Image (tube, grey):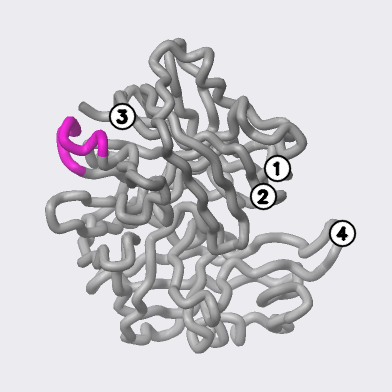
Amino acid sequence: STGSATTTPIDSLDDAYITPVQIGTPAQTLNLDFDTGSSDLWVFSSETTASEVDGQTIYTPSKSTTAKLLSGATWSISYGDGSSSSGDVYTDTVSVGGLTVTGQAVESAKKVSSSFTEDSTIDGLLGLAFSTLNTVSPTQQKTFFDNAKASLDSPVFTADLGYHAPGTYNFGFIDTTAYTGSITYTAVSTKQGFWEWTSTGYAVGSGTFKSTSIDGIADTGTTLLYLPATVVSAYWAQVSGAKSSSSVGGYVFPCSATLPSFTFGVGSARIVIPGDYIDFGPISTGSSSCFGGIQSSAGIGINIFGDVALKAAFVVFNGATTPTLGFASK
Protein backbone atom coordinates (compact mmCIF):
# COMPACT_ATOMS: atom_id res chain seq x y z
CA SER A 1 0.00 0.00 0.00
CA THR A 2 0.87 3.68 -0.21
CA GLY A 3 -0.54 7.02 0.92
CA SER A 4 -0.07 10.59 -0.31
CA ALA A 5 -1.36 13.71 1.42
CA THR A 6 -0.89 17.41 0.90
CA THR A 7 0.54 19.43 3.77
CA THR A 8 -0.30 23.14 3.99
CA PRO A 9 1.35 26.00 5.93
CA ILE A 10 -0.84 27.32 8.76
CA ASP A 11 0.11 30.94 8.11
CA SER A 12 2.15 33.26 5.86
CA LEU A 13 5.38 32.47 7.75
CA ASP A 14 5.26 28.66 7.47
CA ASP A 15 5.16 28.46 11.29
CA ALA A 16 3.88 24.89 10.92
CA TYR A 17 2.17 22.64 8.42
CA ILE A 18 -1.15 20.80 8.68
CA THR A 19 -2.17 17.61 6.93
CA PRO A 20 -5.73 16.25 6.86
CA VAL A 21 -6.22 12.92 8.63
CA GLN A 22 -9.34 10.76 8.66
CA ILE A 23 -10.21 9.25 12.06
CA GLY A 24 -13.03 6.88 12.86
CA THR A 25 -16.16 5.62 11.12
CA PRO A 26 -17.71 7.58 9.55
CA ALA A 27 -14.54 9.58 8.99
CA GLN A 28 -13.84 12.62 11.12
CA THR A 29 -11.24 14.73 9.33
CA LEU A 30 -8.82 16.62 11.56
CA ASN A 31 -5.86 18.73 10.44
CA LEU A 32 -2.79 17.42 12.24
CA ASP A 33 0.79 18.64 12.56
CA PHE A 34 3.01 15.80 11.35
CA ASP A 35 5.97 15.77 13.70
CA THR A 36 9.09 13.66 13.03
CA GLY A 37 10.40 14.82 16.44
CA SER A 38 7.72 13.08 18.55
CA SER A 39 5.81 9.81 18.64
CA ASP A 40 2.26 10.47 19.88
CA LEU A 41 -0.83 10.88 17.69
CA TRP A 42 -3.04 13.12 19.83
CA VAL A 43 -6.14 15.15 19.04
CA PHE A 44 -8.43 17.80 20.37
CA SER A 45 -11.57 15.90 21.31
CA SER A 46 -14.99 15.91 22.94
CA GLU A 47 -13.06 15.24 26.17
CA THR A 48 -10.88 18.35 25.96
CA THR A 49 -11.58 20.89 28.74
CA ALA A 50 -14.04 23.26 27.08
CA SER A 51 -12.19 26.46 28.00
CA GLU A 52 -9.08 25.08 26.26
CA VAL A 53 -10.80 24.62 22.90
CA ASP A 54 -10.89 27.70 20.65
CA GLY A 55 -11.84 26.92 17.05
CA GLN A 56 -10.19 23.51 16.61
CA THR A 57 -12.01 20.58 15.05
CA ILE A 58 -12.52 17.87 17.63
CA TYR A 59 -12.59 14.08 17.48
CA THR A 60 -15.69 12.62 19.16
CA PRO A 61 -15.06 8.93 19.79
CA SER A 62 -18.70 8.27 20.76
CA LYS A 63 -19.66 9.06 17.15
CA SER A 64 -17.21 6.53 15.70
CA THR A 65 -18.45 2.95 15.39
CA THR A 66 -14.86 1.68 15.29
CA ALA A 67 -13.58 3.59 18.36
CA LYS A 68 -12.69 1.58 21.44
CA LEU A 69 -11.41 2.88 24.77
CA LEU A 70 -7.92 1.56 25.44
CA SER A 71 -8.76 0.81 29.01
CA GLY A 72 -6.45 2.23 31.65
CA ALA A 73 -4.16 3.98 29.18
CA THR A 74 -3.13 7.60 29.72
CA TRP A 75 -0.62 9.90 28.06
CA SER A 76 1.18 13.12 28.85
CA ILE A 77 3.70 14.95 26.71
CA SER A 78 5.84 18.06 26.96
CA TYR A 79 7.49 19.54 23.88
CA GLY A 80 10.74 21.44 23.40
CA ASP A 81 8.89 24.74 23.11
CA GLY A 82 7.35 24.31 26.55
CA SER A 83 3.89 23.30 25.35
CA SER A 84 2.11 20.21 26.65
CA SER A 85 -0.99 18.06 26.53
CA SER A 86 -2.41 14.95 28.19
CA GLY A 87 -5.41 12.64 28.32
CA ASP A 88 -6.63 9.11 27.69
CA VAL A 89 -6.54 6.80 24.66
CA TYR A 90 -8.82 5.18 22.11
CA THR A 91 -7.98 2.84 19.27
CA ASP A 92 -9.64 3.63 15.96
CA THR A 93 -9.16 3.54 12.20
CA VAL A 94 -6.85 6.26 10.91
CA SER A 95 -6.23 7.09 7.26
CA VAL A 96 -3.69 9.46 5.73
CA GLY A 97 -3.82 10.16 2.03
CA GLY A 98 -5.55 6.86 1.24
CA LEU A 99 -3.39 4.72 3.55
CA THR A 100 -5.41 3.11 6.34
CA VAL A 101 -4.30 1.74 9.70
CA THR A 102 -6.79 -0.12 11.89
CA GLY A 103 -6.29 -0.20 15.66
CA GLN A 104 -4.22 2.99 15.76
CA ALA A 105 -3.81 4.57 19.20
CA VAL A 106 -5.58 7.94 19.06
CA GLU A 107 -4.67 9.91 22.15
CA SER A 108 -7.58 12.07 23.22
CA ALA A 109 -6.62 15.32 24.95
CA LYS A 110 -8.30 16.14 28.23
CA LYS A 111 -5.92 19.09 28.72
CA VAL A 112 -3.78 21.18 26.37
CA SER A 113 -1.49 24.12 27.13
CA SER A 114 -2.23 27.66 26.04
CA SER A 115 -0.09 27.56 22.89
CA PHE A 116 -2.31 24.78 21.52
CA THR A 117 -5.57 26.49 22.49
CA GLU A 118 -4.39 29.70 20.86
CA ASP A 119 -3.67 28.03 17.53
CA SER A 120 -7.05 27.36 15.97
CA THR A 121 -5.53 25.77 12.86
CA ILE A 122 -3.88 22.71 14.50
CA ASP A 123 -6.28 19.98 15.66
CA GLY A 124 -3.51 17.75 17.06
CA LEU A 125 -0.18 16.11 16.29
CA LEU A 126 0.78 12.97 14.41
CA GLY A 127 4.17 11.75 15.62
CA LEU A 128 6.61 10.18 13.19
CA ALA A 129 9.70 9.70 15.38
CA PHE A 130 10.48 6.24 16.77
CA SER A 131 7.82 4.51 18.87
CA THR A 132 10.23 4.26 21.81
CA LEU A 133 9.32 7.92 22.54
CA ASN A 134 5.57 7.28 22.68
CA THR A 135 4.21 8.45 26.07
CA VAL A 136 1.24 6.10 26.52
CA SER A 137 1.27 4.33 29.88
CA PRO A 138 1.25 1.57 31.01
CA THR A 139 1.42 0.07 27.50
CA GLN A 140 3.47 2.11 25.03
CA GLN A 141 1.84 2.50 21.63
CA LYS A 142 3.13 2.50 18.06
CA THR A 143 3.18 5.44 15.66
CA PHE A 144 1.03 5.52 12.55
CA PHE A 145 4.14 4.81 10.43
CA ASP A 146 5.23 1.90 12.63
CA ASN A 147 1.75 0.37 12.36
CA ALA A 148 1.58 0.90 8.58
CA LYS A 149 5.13 -0.19 7.78
CA ALA A 150 4.64 -3.88 7.08
CA SER A 151 1.83 -3.11 4.61
CA LEU A 152 3.71 -0.40 2.73
CA ASP A 153 5.26 -1.11 -0.66
CA SER A 154 8.54 0.18 0.83
CA PRO A 155 9.14 0.97 4.52
CA VAL A 156 9.58 4.71 4.02
CA PHE A 157 7.87 8.04 4.21
CA THR A 158 8.93 11.30 2.60
CA ALA A 159 8.57 14.96 3.56
CA ASP A 160 8.40 17.56 0.81
CA LEU A 161 7.58 20.80 2.58
CA GLY A 162 6.88 23.95 0.60
CA TYR A 163 8.23 27.46 1.08
CA HIS A 164 5.13 29.63 1.50
CA ALA A 165 3.26 26.89 -0.41
CA PRO A 166 1.72 23.45 0.08
CA GLY A 167 3.83 20.31 -0.05
CA THR A 168 3.44 16.56 0.34
CA TYR A 169 3.86 13.67 2.75
CA ASN A 170 4.10 10.30 0.99
CA PHE A 171 4.04 6.89 2.62
CA GLY A 172 5.46 3.73 1.08
CA PHE A 173 7.08 5.12 -2.07
CA ILE A 174 9.61 7.63 -3.32
CA ASP A 175 8.21 10.02 -5.96
CA THR A 176 11.12 10.29 -8.37
CA THR A 177 9.51 13.34 -10.03
CA ALA A 178 9.57 15.37 -6.80
CA TYR A 179 13.31 16.10 -6.62
CA THR A 180 16.28 16.97 -8.83
CA GLY A 181 19.56 15.08 -9.06
CA SER A 182 20.11 12.14 -6.73
CA ILE A 183 19.15 11.39 -3.13
CA THR A 184 22.08 11.23 -0.73
CA TYR A 185 21.53 8.85 2.17
CA THR A 186 23.16 9.24 5.56
CA ALA A 187 23.25 7.15 8.75
CA VAL A 188 20.70 7.53 11.55
CA SER A 189 21.07 6.89 15.26
CA THR A 190 17.83 5.89 16.96
CA LYS A 191 19.41 5.92 20.43
CA GLN A 192 17.44 9.00 21.53
CA GLY A 193 14.28 8.01 19.59
CA PHE A 194 14.80 10.68 16.91
CA TRP A 195 15.80 10.73 13.25
CA GLU A 196 19.28 11.76 14.40
CA TRP A 197 22.04 12.19 11.85
CA THR A 198 25.33 14.04 11.33
CA SER A 199 25.68 16.84 8.82
CA THR A 200 29.13 17.18 7.26
CA GLY A 201 29.34 20.98 7.51
CA TYR A 202 28.04 24.31 6.32
CA ALA A 203 28.56 27.42 4.27
CA VAL A 204 27.22 30.95 4.60
CA GLY A 205 26.16 32.63 1.36
CA SER A 206 28.83 32.27 -1.31
CA GLY A 207 31.44 31.53 1.36
CA THR A 208 33.69 28.50 1.51
CA PHE A 209 32.32 25.27 2.94
CA LYS A 210 33.42 24.42 6.48
CA SER A 211 33.82 20.69 7.00
CA THR A 212 32.62 19.92 10.50
CA SER A 213 30.36 17.25 12.00
CA ILE A 214 27.02 18.57 13.25
CA ASP A 215 24.83 15.99 14.99
CA GLY A 216 21.14 16.85 14.93
CA ILE A 217 17.60 15.70 14.32
CA ALA A 218 15.34 15.97 11.29
CA ASP A 219 12.26 17.48 12.90
CA THR A 220 9.25 18.52 10.83
CA GLY A 221 7.48 19.72 13.99
CA THR A 222 10.06 22.43 14.71
CA THR A 223 9.77 25.64 12.69
CA LEU A 224 13.37 26.88 12.71
CA LEU A 225 16.93 25.65 12.22
CA TYR A 226 18.78 25.38 15.54
CA LEU A 227 22.56 24.96 15.29
CA PRO A 228 25.65 25.48 17.47
CA ALA A 229 26.32 29.04 18.56
CA THR A 230 29.56 29.18 16.55
CA VAL A 231 27.71 28.35 13.30
CA VAL A 232 24.84 30.72 14.02
CA SER A 233 27.19 33.60 14.87
CA ALA A 234 29.06 33.04 11.59
CA TYR A 235 25.77 33.26 9.69
CA TRP A 236 24.40 36.43 11.32
CA ALA A 237 27.78 38.18 11.15
CA GLN A 238 27.09 38.43 7.40
CA VAL A 239 23.91 40.47 7.96
CA SER A 240 24.46 44.16 8.77
CA GLY A 241 22.74 45.10 11.99
CA ALA A 242 21.86 41.56 13.06
CA LYS A 243 22.15 40.84 16.76
CA SER A 244 21.14 38.36 19.40
CA SER A 245 18.42 39.82 21.58
CA SER A 246 17.84 38.28 25.00
CA SER A 247 14.59 40.25 25.26
CA VAL A 248 13.21 38.91 21.97
CA GLY A 249 14.64 35.42 22.45
CA GLY A 250 17.16 35.06 19.64
CA TYR A 251 18.74 36.66 16.64
CA VAL A 252 16.92 39.53 15.02
CA PHE A 253 17.89 41.51 11.95
CA PRO A 254 16.80 44.67 10.13
CA CYS A 255 13.77 43.93 7.99
CA SER A 256 15.49 45.95 5.23
CA ALA A 257 18.24 43.29 4.92
CA THR A 258 18.77 40.86 2.10
CA LEU A 259 19.63 37.56 3.82
CA PRO A 260 22.38 35.26 2.55
CA SER A 261 21.72 31.60 1.87
CA PHE A 262 22.85 28.85 4.21
CA THR A 263 24.21 25.52 2.95
CA PHE A 264 24.38 22.31 4.95
CA GLY A 265 26.21 19.12 4.07
CA VAL A 266 24.74 15.66 3.65
CA GLY A 267 27.72 13.43 3.02
CA SER A 268 29.45 14.92 0.00
CA ALA A 269 26.18 16.56 -1.11
CA ARG A 270 24.96 20.06 -0.28
CA ILE A 271 21.49 21.46 0.46
CA VAL A 272 21.09 25.20 -0.06
CA ILE A 273 18.57 27.13 2.03
CA PRO A 274 17.76 30.39 0.20
CA GLY A 275 18.04 33.54 2.29
CA ASP A 276 14.31 34.26 2.04
CA TYR A 277 13.58 30.99 3.90
CA ILE A 278 15.42 32.45 6.92
CA ASP A 279 13.10 35.50 7.21
CA PHE A 280 10.39 35.09 9.88
CA GLY A 281 9.16 38.64 9.62
CA PRO A 282 8.58 41.46 12.09
CA ILE A 283 8.98 40.53 15.75
CA SER A 284 5.71 42.36 16.42
CA THR A 285 3.25 43.91 14.00
CA GLY A 286 4.75 46.98 12.33
CA SER A 287 8.25 46.47 13.70
CA SER A 288 11.30 46.94 11.50
CA SER A 289 13.13 44.24 13.47
CA CYS A 290 12.67 40.82 11.92
CA PHE A 291 13.10 37.41 13.53
CA GLY A 292 15.76 35.07 12.20
CA GLY A 293 15.12 31.53 11.02
CA ILE A 294 18.53 30.23 12.12
CA GLN A 295 18.95 30.27 15.90
CA SER A 296 21.33 28.86 18.47
CA SER A 297 20.73 25.39 19.90
CA ALA A 298 22.80 26.25 22.99
CA GLY A 299 20.78 25.17 26.00
CA ILE A 300 18.37 23.02 23.96
CA GLY A 301 20.85 20.20 24.23
CA ILE A 302 20.45 19.10 20.62
CA ASN A 303 20.73 20.60 17.14
CA ILE A 304 17.45 20.66 15.23
CA PHE A 305 17.06 20.58 11.45
CA GLY A 306 13.53 21.98 11.51
CA ASP A 307 11.31 23.19 8.72
CA VAL A 308 13.66 25.99 7.59
CA ALA A 309 16.17 23.32 6.61
CA LEU A 310 13.84 20.51 5.59
CA LYS A 311 11.71 22.59 3.24
CA ALA A 312 14.82 23.21 1.11
CA ALA A 313 14.98 19.46 0.39
CA PHE A 314 13.09 16.34 -0.53
CA VAL A 315 13.62 14.20 2.59
CA VAL A 316 13.36 10.41 2.83
CA PHE A 317 12.70 8.85 6.22
CA ASN A 318 13.82 5.28 5.58
CA GLY A 319 12.40 2.94 8.20
CA ALA A 320 14.15 -0.21 7.03
CA THR A 321 15.69 -2.51 9.66
CA THR A 322 18.63 -0.11 9.83
CA PRO A 323 17.02 3.31 9.36
CA THR A 324 18.62 6.04 7.26
CA LEU A 325 17.76 9.54 6.04
CA GLY A 326 17.94 10.75 2.46
CA PHE A 327 18.16 14.30 1.17
CA ALA A 328 17.79 15.61 -2.37
CA SER A 329 17.61 19.10 -3.81
CA LYS A 330 14.33 20.02 -5.52
Q: Amino acid at mark 2?
A: Ser
State left or right for residue 125 relative to residue 187. Answer: right
Please tell me which residue is depicted at 72% across the width and 31% down the height of the picture: 55
Residue 112 lies in quadrant? top right
Please tell me which residue is depicted at 57% across the width and 42% down the height of the picture: 9
Q: Amino acid at mark 3?
A: Gly
In the rendered image, residue 150, in percent from the top left (x then y), is placed at 16, 35
Q: Earlier in the sequence, mark 3 or mark 1?
A: 3
State left or right for residue 41 relative to residue 165. Answer: left
Report how far apart the C-alphas of labels 1 and 2 lie in the structure: 7 Å
Report how far apart the C-alphas of labels 2 and 4 lie in the structure: 28 Å
The magenta stretch is 147-155
Q: Earlier in the sequence, mark 3 or mark 4?
A: 3
Residue identified by numbered label 4: 286
Q: Nearer the viewer, mark 3 or mark 1?
A: 1
Report how far apart the C-alphas of labels 3 and 4 lie in the structure: 42 Å
In the displayed structure, 251 sits above or below 234; it is above
Report how far apart the C-alphas of labels 3 and 1 lie in the structure: 29 Å
